[PDB]
Image (cartoon, coloured by chain):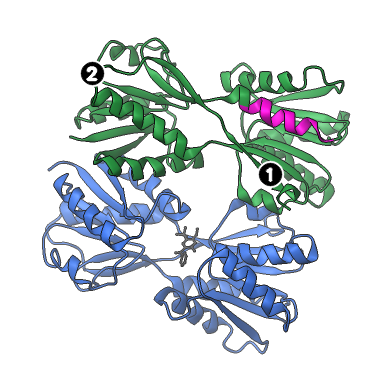
Chain colours: A green, B blue
Amino acid sequence: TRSIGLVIPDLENTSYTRIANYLERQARQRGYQLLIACSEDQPDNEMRCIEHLLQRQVDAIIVSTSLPPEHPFYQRWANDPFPIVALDRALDREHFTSVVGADQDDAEMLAEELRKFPAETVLYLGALPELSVSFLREQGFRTAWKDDPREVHFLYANSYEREAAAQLFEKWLETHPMPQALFTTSFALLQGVMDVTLRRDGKLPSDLAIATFGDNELLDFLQCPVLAVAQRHRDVAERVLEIVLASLDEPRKPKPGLTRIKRNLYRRGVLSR
Amino acid sequence: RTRSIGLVIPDLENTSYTRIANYLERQARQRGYQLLIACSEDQPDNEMRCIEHLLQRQVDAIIVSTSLPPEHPFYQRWANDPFPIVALDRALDREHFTSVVGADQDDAEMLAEELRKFPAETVLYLGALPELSVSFLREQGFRTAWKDDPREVHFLYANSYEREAAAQLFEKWLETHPMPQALFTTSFALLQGVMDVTLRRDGKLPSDLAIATFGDNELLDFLQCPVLAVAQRHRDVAERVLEIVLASLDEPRKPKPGLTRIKRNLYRRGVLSR
Ligand SMILES: COc1cc(O)c(C(=O)c2ccccc2)cc1S(=O)(=O)O
């Protein structure tokens, strides 16, 4: 049918949507169509989303899976010429080619740059440390702060939400002082922090080195140094499809496993002037 | 029947269209239809090729935000055909096509009326391309409110709905004009441009500047000045677009052709959020 599937959580998170843009422009570039099927990050929906695509004779499916990488569903096409390429969330490494992010290196690069700033109190706010993205990003931080003499207080929330971040930061400040360097592993985490700072200070900070995953351009309006990393949204889209159309239009299928694209760093706030 | 519906939009980078698309996918998935998406890149020539491809996929219907003028001859091929094509955002031939569209006049007036309740002497209306249908209706609504208001309103108009344009024009305007106590912008982009110069000048984003804009962004909550923003009822829109798509198909006769307008929601941000 000359059509490719893309099962993502939703067309609302900016990361997935901007990739899906450069994937439309490059799908129609080669004559193929893109059929978006959202799971709302529900494994029940994703399983059915996939099933409805097979019924539409899609030639290939790119997927950011909500289920475990190794789980009975996807091991149905473990040994199948039917290609399933993973994005952002890896699948079984021995059976599927996944294009993922370089969270560890990315965290390290961001952390190295934050370390140069002359803070005393340095706070690391993350969430769900038991998870992969959470831990990979912690290692990256520690790598760059390994032999640094300053003590970094780590603080972990129950989810990557701003509501949670508000509470946990609001509590933290009772028994700790306002930090001078901040490393947040999500943009949503940083929002929570700012909410409380706005109520406490009456104004968003001007003497604080912020470092965060995820990037909005409105961070240029801050009057403090801001460091932020974002995906190479086009570059990500190139490789996911170049693996799809390798599996279709060549005898040798691509070798399974992971492949990583680094994030870009952006200087926002006062560092943009 | 294939149980598929085409969707031709400018791009998937504009936040309006993407959020409309998100809900359209869900609404369609719930009803038992797949959604095929094709971006025109807002090029008229590309749009035509998209419609052709989508018809070879043999969809039951096509939604389109068209880059052609209403009445344009290309879309007279299906002027009077049972096959349904439902226009989104930008209207098609009102005679023989149903268009889900915003009430830019109604929204503008309502937003303007809210901006009148702040005690601001100088009131700057910044717009762009006044002669465009959209630009016009919004200015029309603004005057319907400030009809008998004794204060003077300065109407500044830019060459493009873009940030950089608004920045240059505003900073050349301040040269001879005092700093406004009230602002009305017809797009977030124009607002952005204003906020650059305010920052380059004052040193900080302001606190005593009543602001009313088209476009929305939750991050407007962080401002310490009053803010008023209008945005489409994306979900409500998405619902009503597909209702027509299906009524058109699942119901004898297509609904009354022409326009149905949907008012934006107003949100309160800055210090209005606390
Ligand atoms: C995010 O809010 C919006 C902001 C807008 O500026 C528009 C426009 O239609 C528009 C009109 C003239 C020039 C440029 C854009 C729509 C929405 S909305 O659909 O998302 O409510």
Question: Is the residue at mark 1 in contact range of ligand 1, meaning its CB lies under 8 Å from it?
Answer: no
Residue type, label 2: Pro
Question: Is B201 drawn above or below residue A169 in the view shown?
Answer: below
> Is disc 2 surrounded by few (<14), some (14 to 19) or many (20+) residues within 10 Å?
few
Query: What residue is shown at x 69% (from left), y 73% (from top)?
Result: B171
Q: Chain of mark 1?
A: A
Instruction: Determine if the magenta segment contains residue A110.
Output: yes
Q: Where is mark 1, residue-wise?
A: A267
Q: Classify mark 2: helix, strand or loop.
A: loop
The segment highlighted magenta reads A106-117
Residue A99, horizontal then vertical, whole percent: 44, 25
> Is disc 1 surrounded by few (<14), some (14 to 19) or many (20+) residues within 10 Å?
some
Q: Chain of mark 2?
A: A
**Viewer-side residue, B244 vs B174:** B174
Question: Is B236 drawn above or below residue A246 in the view shown?
Answer: below
Q: Along the polypeptide, which appears first: circle 1 or circle 2?
A: 2
Quadrant location of residue A5? top left
Question: Is A249 drawn above or below residue A257 in the view shown?
Answer: below
Q: Is residue A91 visible?
A: yes
Q: Where is mark 2, residue-wise?
A: A251
- Determine whether, in the image, residue A108 is placed left or right of residue A99: right
